[PDB]
Length: 177
Length: 177
Ligand code: NI
Ligand code: NI
Picture 1 (tube, rainbow over the protein chains, first blue to last red):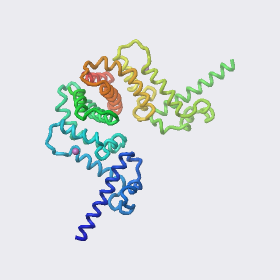
Picture 2 (cartoon, rainbow over the protein chains, first blue to last red):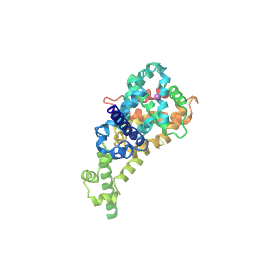
Picture 3 (cartoon, rainbow over the protein chains, first blue to last red):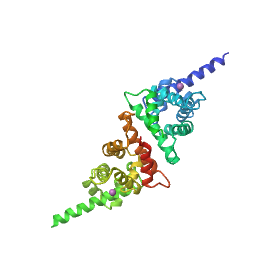
Picture 4 (cartoon, rainbow over the protein chains, first blue to last red):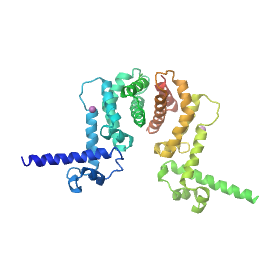
């Protein structure tokens, strides 16, 4: 219909902003970009942006929300380490600036990300790779999660990076117990 | 000896500021500190503060050469483990505000610190505790250093900290591959 077409048009403009925000997050810190940057790409004016997004803050939120739903909140039937590999797969191509988001140190992205790791990566990592029990649980939790995040950051700064499977390997052997 | 008297007054003023700077670092962190606050505590004039230190940076500099010379490059006749106990012992007590520098996240301290581990802790840690060329060196090095620094940071953010003995032990039985 004639409302069918206007809808299809508000849906394409919402995506333009979304995609603009991502492309700009490839070159800049979240703290460093401004709504005018976001328009200058989206080609949609100040008034309409604010009709979809209360502020820049809900793009980060939405984005993350999306990025983390695709990484973890999958019921995609695979082995634990296929699951790890897929996660790492996204980082190495910087699927939607996810790498740049992590390397930027944006405190908010680093927070919600560490929290997903706690819910969907740690419990399996624990039960499946750590066999002994002479190291307390909290030290375990902290050493494991933090060394995962740090292995990952280091790999992303690497100009010549190992295959995701090599890194997943060298990490799992480093921590297994 | 009135030039001997003059030197003596210079010296007393200089450490008087240096001590104040350390004191302010116990709570507030480096970036949030001013000449006002240092001189208020050191009970000194702004003109005199400046004939001693170009700025609050040359203080951070000097404080840093001091702490590491002490922590690391000491030719004390101890075994590698005693050595690390002494380093951990400093952070446990916040000796010269050192625990607070680290937890402050200040680029300058952190950068200098890491560089010192790299040079004085990593070589022995890896030789003494790693007996498996199963893993490539660079990966090995990145992983040990980050695990140390973060286990350090983690321990320090603890409400009821564990003993430096338990920490070093759990750390070491964790990387020992
Ligand atoms: Ni995918
Ligand atoms: Ni000492």
